[PDB]
Amino acid sequence: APQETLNGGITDMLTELANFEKNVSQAIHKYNAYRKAASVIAKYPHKIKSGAEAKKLPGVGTKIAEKIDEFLATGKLRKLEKIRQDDTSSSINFLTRVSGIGPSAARKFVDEGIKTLEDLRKNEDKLNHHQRIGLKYFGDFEKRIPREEMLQMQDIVLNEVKKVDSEYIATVCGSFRRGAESSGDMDVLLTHPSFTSESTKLLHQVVEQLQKVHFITDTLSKGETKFMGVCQLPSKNDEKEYPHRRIDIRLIPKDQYYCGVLYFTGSDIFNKNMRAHALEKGFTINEYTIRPLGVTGVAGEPLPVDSEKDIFDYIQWKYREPKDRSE
DNA sequence: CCGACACCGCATCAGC
DNA sequence: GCTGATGCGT
DNA sequence: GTCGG
Ligand code: NA
Ligand code: NA
Ligand code: NA
Ligand code: NA
């Protein structure tokens, strides 16, 4: 985990570029290209001396190598400096930081003169439900969640779920499950023996109880299988109130639950490699199932999975702890 | 050279 | 009103 | 923007 001081200037630059591609130029693939470049460089255990050196890293190509050369010789990048001062682009880029406001909404807003949160605040009528909530908790949503708070949050979630029906199975996934010391939000995977792929309010009852005890404070979206909202830990009489947090709850069929827990636990890298290894072993693993691949490439019916290990067993790969799934 | 870069639930829009 | 497409987010 | 069939 090389200190940012190594190539932080370079990594910051690529990430800033990444954001403008995504939020202003609406070029999602260039956005991911810059992210990938910044990721590989952020991991590089050496202070980069030239673009040629960086180009050796997978994800860093001709254009980025050239930009690195400019940054190393001048300490900046003309194209980035210019776009920072651009009132329109900087505003569009900024507005996307509000949950619910994507590249399209941000452009539409800036086009009609709405460029700041203050502007947004004065124009509630132009915001949909999600966006109003995103505006309401703008600061809180950008704050991270200490593991200690994630544990208290888990305590409430697991308690209320069991209270609704002791047969529910709930698992808080994400980096939190891998042992991370901080999380950006809470991702809860829920299932019930009564719910399977080929079988016929399970989610509603849980969301409702969480609201009843005033843990869940707002709802961004809610259907029969996925809830996205806001929650807040109860504050101690006198204590500063805790920040509002983003929490998602997904109801998944029992027979596909562990493939789900596996995937949403990550990391994104571990998923890539495991899915790779699975292929060569003659298996295709996605978010919902693991299936065998015949000699001509024809996928067969999904294999029974009753635990994460079952998945690991199928592809000959000793079960690895979540704490060791960094890659 | 030029297509891939993931799949999908929900809220909401666009077209009929 | 219904159906499909789009925006957004994870 | 980068990769690769
Ligand atoms: Na490269
Ligand atoms: Na946003
Ligand atoms: Na954003
Ligand atoms: Na019971």
Image (cartoon, coloured by chain):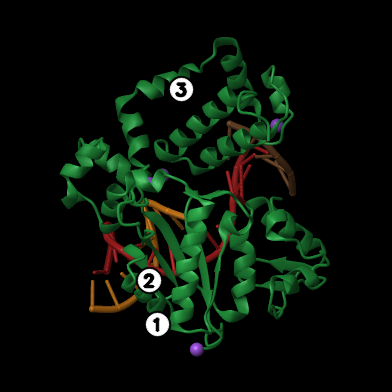
Chain colours: A green, B red, C orange, D brown
Residue on which disc 2 sits? A210
A1 is higher (above) or lower (below) than A241: above
Residue on which disc 1 sits? A201
Measure how far apart labels 3 and 1 are at the Cα level: 50 Å
User: Where does residue A314 sit, x and y in percent of width and height?
Assistant: 79, 72
**Front one among A235 and A293:** A235
Image mark 1: chain: A
Residue on which disc 3 sits? A80
Three-letter code for the amino acid on which mark 1 is drawn = Lys
Three-letter code for the amino acid on which mark 3 is drawn = Leu
User: Where does residue A190 sit, x and y in percent of width and height?
Assistant: 51, 73
A88 is higher (above) or lower (below) than A133: above
User: Where does residue A128 sit, x and y in percent of width and height?
Assistant: 25, 55
**Quadrant of the rendered structure where residue A256 is?**
bottom right
Considering only order in the chain, which callout, 1 or 2, is on the residue closer to the N terminus?
1
- Viewed as shown, does residue A78 lie left or right of A69? left
Q: Visible in this render: residue A298?
A: no
